[PDB]
Amino acid sequence: STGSATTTPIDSLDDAYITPVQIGTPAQTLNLDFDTGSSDLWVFSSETTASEVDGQTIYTPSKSTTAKLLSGATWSISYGDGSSSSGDVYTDTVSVGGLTVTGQAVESAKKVSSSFTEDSTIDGLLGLAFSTLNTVSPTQQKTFFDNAKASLDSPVFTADLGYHAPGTYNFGFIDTTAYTGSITYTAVSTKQGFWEWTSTGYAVGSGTFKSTSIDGIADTGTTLLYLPATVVSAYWAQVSGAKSSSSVGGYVFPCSATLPSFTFGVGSARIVIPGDYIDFGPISTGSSSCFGGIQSSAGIGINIFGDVALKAAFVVFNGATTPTLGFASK
């Protein structure tokens, strides 16, 4: 089997992407944030504290003839950005782009943090990291991909995120029309539960390539590119007037600037992030200070190849017995 679904930016900055997901019988379609940095499929629901729901579409398990309470199971998650959610668990039928999993754990939120409430466009998350990170207790549950994998034509999914435009998540096949040149594959460590890999270096603009190993994670659920402070300083030094602002919470730059590109290495291959992908716009409405899309990972504890990086590539998440990651230009 295969599946193919369009993923759509939630706003004009590509702050996140939402993908429609069918849950239950009859289908209830929710727009979920596909997150290769976590491993829980959780939704706003009829159980979510009413004051914490503000415009989201909810899953109502009592209206699904295939929903079953997973007795005694609870979940609770905290994300790198400080947001969180928790609740109980149902199993139900879940379909993405024509690919159906029966008996998928659907984690129903009883509580969500303010950041989730305040974002009316995201009805929940669909985790695509390794199932070892799943938070369900006392019986850990599998991700949608893990459940689907054996049925897929090939045990892979691909992320093809758009810049200021829709893109595609495919399951079970590689669309050879969706990228240019070849796909370069690179080793993955699953030791921390992430799609963790090592970039071979970077360049700023038309500058020379610096060969240096940068361990980090491919994370569709993180907006920005978080890299070591040395790399980030080298980038922003090429933008007149850019500075790190403790008050704003990262590098800012004059909105009048033209940003240089940023290149990262995948083996001997190179992925170029155009300068415009690194612009996250005014820090507040009407400001002439703009927020940068490349930020320091210092104090996160891990480097994160988030959407800024991934949307410059066609990315293969290869879930074979020994997982790997592939990147192609597009």
Image (cartoon, rainbow, N blue to C red):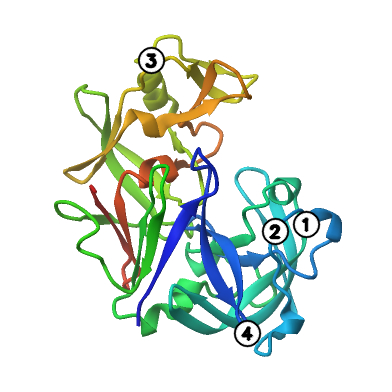
Foreground of the two, 79 or 193: 79
**Where residue 120 sits in the image (x, y, percent)?**
68, 51
Which label sits on residue 133? none
Foreground of the two, 138 or 288: 288
Camera sees residue 91: yes
| Left/right of residue 118 with respect to residue 16 in the rendered view | right
**Where residue 159 sits in the image (x, y, percent)?**
37, 58
Which residue extends farthest left? Answer: 181
* Residues at marks 3 and 1, CA–CA distance in whole angstroms: 41 Å
Mark 3–mark 1 CB contact (< 8 Å): no
Residue found at x 61% / y 67%: 30
**Residue where numbered disc 3 is placed:** 239
Secondary structure under the numbered disc 3 in the rendered image: loop
Residue found at x 64% / y 82%: 91
Secondary structure under the numbered disc 2 in the rendered image: loop
**Residue where numbered disc 1 is placed:** 53
Q: Amino acid at mark 2?
A: Gln
Camera sees residue 191: no
Circle 3: is it few (<14), some (14-19), or many (20+) Cα within 10 Å? some
**Residue where numbered disc 2 is placed:** 56
Mark 3–mark 4 CB contact (< 8 Å): no
**Where residue 20 sits in the image (x, y, percent)?**
53, 66
**Where residue 42 sits in the image (x, y, percent)?**
64, 66
Mark 1–mark 2 CB contact (< 8 Å): yes
Residue found at x 31% / y 72%: 320
Q: Amino acid at mark 1?
A: Val
